[PDB]
Amino acid sequence: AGRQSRTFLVDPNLDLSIRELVHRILPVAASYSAVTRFIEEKSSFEYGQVNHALAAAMRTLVKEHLILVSQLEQLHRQGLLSLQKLWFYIQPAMRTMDILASLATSVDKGECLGGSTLSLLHDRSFSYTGDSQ
Amino acid sequence: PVLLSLLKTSCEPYTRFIHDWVYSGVFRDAYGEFMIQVNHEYLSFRDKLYWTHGYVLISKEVEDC
Amino acid sequence: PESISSLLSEVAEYGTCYTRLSHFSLQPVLDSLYSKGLVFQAFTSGLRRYLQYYRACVLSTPPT
Amino acid sequence: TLFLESVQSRLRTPKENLMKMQSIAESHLELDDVHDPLLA
Amino acid sequence: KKVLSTEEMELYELAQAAGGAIDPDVFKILVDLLKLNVAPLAVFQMLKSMCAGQRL
Amino acid sequence: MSEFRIHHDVNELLSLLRVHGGDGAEVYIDLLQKNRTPYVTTTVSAHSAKVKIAEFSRTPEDFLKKYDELKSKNTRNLDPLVYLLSKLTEDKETLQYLQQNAKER
């Protein structure tokens, strides 16, 4: 619905603990969907070269995310992925995608271009003084 | 040990603010946690008042600041 | 069942502490409405790490 | 003790924990979370 | 409200939520003063000096 | 912007505040210009300023939510505006006078 993050519907007949763990993991998929929409929108020439380069850099991290998700799929095919193991292993990916979705949302809400995008990126980089990753 | 770790982790942003304050006189306290506040109107002053009021250390509650 | 209930009550108290502490530490983002400051936000990040370690320990507990 | 030892002799009578914790963390912690040694 | 820009309008809505019923033209001029990178402490001192003489 | 935009803005503010006499407009201009830095060097603790306004705001939740909204938009002068509002909330007399002028205006 609009420029909102993607929401997911989980089957109500799933176990409550399973359903809650899915809802904890789904934020990664919501962030990925938000980042992909941001990447696809801000990759337009009209968004300027800084926003295009930002979208390409985000696309590289989304590609790494797809590699990670493909690894989780491969582990699942091997039966090595439990919901608790997925939740633990996705914690870094969940945080990365949440940061990417927050940046995507901030760039899109501020209509940042050129020096305003660099200003926003500087303020975000300062805002992450406590998170080295 | 866990309390020491948590104290270190919580001081890390505060230690960064302290570093910026000490090296550049830049108050990097986003939440007003540092004992020094900068009143920029007098920081632009080119007299004694620049030093006294441009950046003000909260002195009354030194223990709290 | 009464003694088992007592043991389970103690275990439930520990689980209650875990879940409530996780919720308290779960205050995630130092957003502009976060008034506790960056030291508190970093503390909550460390607490999230601690709770992650706790979850890891719980999962490391063999069900046998 | 000296008496007992002498009597028996005459009668011919009668970091590693940190490493274990690190291995446990590696087996149960996600790769990217730095172990805190005081917390560890 | 037409005196204030959309960003200035959003700041005016925020100021109203802050409890400040400010005139949109006064808020617009204040935003223009803030756009000139004037220190807000000096702007506050200026406002105080301008208001102190006007007894209700 | 015009070199003398500050003089127009000050004259408008004097007219809007019904300040009798342009005697001293030069003093207000000189105060603002002497304390006007071309760079936003004042790292204002917006969190504490937000807190002061929320204690001052009749709608503190709305103030905090709007601050986080404007920050997510990277809205310029947000923290300066919140600081200005906090300083007006500190000066109850100035705030009452401004409210009465706004009502009269």
Image (spheres, rainbow, N blue to C red):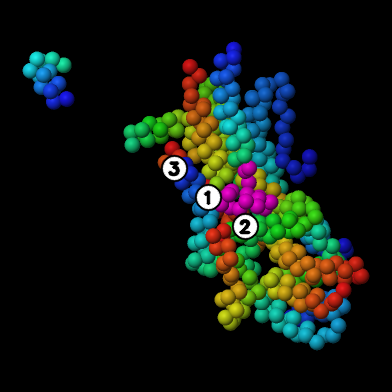
- Label 3: how many Cα within 10 Å (few below 14, some 14–19, many 20+): few
Look at the image and give the residue range highlighted in magenta. C27-42
Q: Residue at x 84, y 71 (%)?
A: F97
* Residue furthest to the bottom: F23
| Disc 2, SS | loop
Describe residue A63's horizontal placement relative to residue D31 as left or right. right
3D distance between C-alphas at marks 1 and 2: 13 Å
Residue at which label 3 appears: B1
Name the chain letter of the residue that bears numbered label 2. Answer: B
Give x and y (percent) for residue F2: 76, 78
Name the amino acid type tagged 2: Tyr
Name the chain letter of the residue that bears numbered label 3. Answer: B
- Label 2: how many Cα within 10 Å (few below 14, some 14–19, many 20+): many
Residue at which label 1 appears: B10
Labels 2 & 3 near each other (Cβ < 8 A): no
Give x and y (percent) for residue E27: 81, 67
Q: Are marks 1 and 2 on the same chain?
A: yes
| Residue F84 visible in the current orientation | no
Q: Which mark is residue B31?
A: 2
Residue F84 magenta: no
